Image: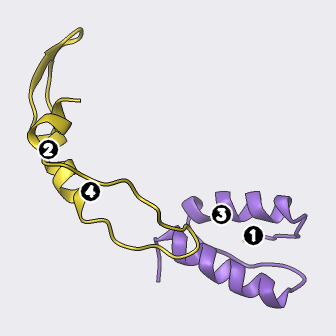
Chain colours: A purple, B yellow
Amino acid sequence: NLFDSFEASRRACDQLALGVAALFGPSHSSSVSAVQSICNALEVPHIQT
Amino acid sequence: AIASHRASQLTVSSLQCHRHKPWRLGPRFMNLIKEARWDGLTGRITFNKT
């Protein structure tokens, strides 16, 4: 569901527990800030559309 | 400080940030602050409910 960047963070943690080559989304600016911050923190590719 | 006046005693948090848990005193603190009127340096200070 949209909003609630906290569950988006939970989803990102769960995904990186697996680990992939790139990330898609989220579609709202609030989450993407933390997403890019953590992608840089773990040095992680991220692409947005 | 003035919001802390009208409320009862409270405790501090010890919650993790991996998973969130509700905080019941937050809403009552919210009611305290948003309906408290005060006279200050910038004149009258008022808070809305929108």
The residue under label 2 is which amino acid type? Leu
The residue that mark 2 highlights is B32
Residue A13 higher or lower than B48, as above or below:
below
The residue under label 4 is which amino acid type? Gly
Please state, as top left, top right, bottom left or bottom right, where the N terminus of chain B lies in the image: top left
Marks 3 and 1 close (CB-CB < 8 Å): yes
Task: Determine the image quadrant of residue A16.
Answer: bottom right
To the question of a shared chain for discs 1 and 4, the answer is no
Q: Earlier in the sequence, mark 4 or mark 2?
A: 4
On residue A48, the disc is: 1
Badge 2 local density, few (<14 within 10 Å), some, or many (20+)?
Answer: some
Label 1 is found on which chain of the structure?
A: A
Residue A20 higher or lower than B46, as above or below:
below
On residue A32, the disc is: 3
The residue under label 1 is which amino acid type? Gln
To the question of a shared chain for discs 2 and 1, the answer is no
Could you tell whether A3 is left or right of A15 in the image?
Answer: left
Task: Determine the image quadrant of residue A40.
Answer: bottom right
Badge 1 local density, few (<14 within 10 Å), some, or many (20+)?
Answer: few
Residue B27 higher or lower than A45, as above or below:
above
Element under disc 3: helix
Foreground disc of the pair 1, 4: 4
Marks 2 and 1 close (CB-CB < 8 Å): no
